[PDB]
Image 1 (cartoon, rainbow, N blue to C red):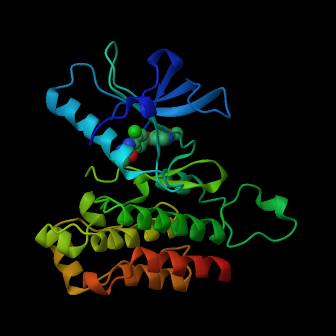
Image 2: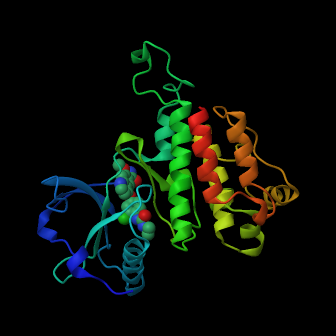
Length: 278
Ligand SMILES: COc1cc2nccc(Oc3ccc(NC(=O)NC4CC4)c(Cl)c3)c2cc1C(N)=O
């Protein structure tokens, strides 16, 4: 996996480094990274001061994942990197103003209606079922993309979905991986990670969406009994903002047999249908 400096290298002196976000990720403004804007706000992952060789390797590996994967609207995309001598290793990605989707949805619990009714200004900036189904559809499209690149996410969860402007959501932290609440039974018991175990996790992500950012498995200690009951077929109950069709979609993603779960291409088609029906 070679590094194409002519494509990706960005001058460190064309960044204004700002506040920490959320690794050592900071907000920054970049000057001339984008031909349509003089100044563009970006997120920068910077190698810690005193990083070990292993830690340095790891951030470089992350950069090469971002290069290799390619561009998609629903994935957090690489804009540039600072790799040359005279400063820290820095990985520059698109900025997602609203941050992670779990935190964001929780902030909107008192600003949700199933659909707006005229006069719609009574629901200014409210979330709706359309928003939630739309976020779901977008994540399915991003995972279909990742699957097509032979990439398994391994920790698909609402905390790893970022919200940008214009209700665009972006998957992050793919290929890098509490955690047990998103893991398919085969992952927990057999340590098998596949695109079908990501589909299971997508199911959990859907529950997080349609609970407006709740933590999965409320009231349950994540221990051997949790794992045993999951294996025996027990599943989360319908969350507070779901439609019946979306709940059935969760159940489908949680089929005990990985081969009987929908594919992400099937989920894109299905959610796209649910979105037009809604
Ligand atoms: C406003 O809050 C945030 C905005 C962000 N925008 C873009 C990227 C972010 O963070 C990330 C999130 C992930 C990656 N890296 C990857 O996704 N790497 C994996 C693909 C190889 C990077 Cl660099 C930066 C952001 C984080 C916050 C925040 N409050 O947490």
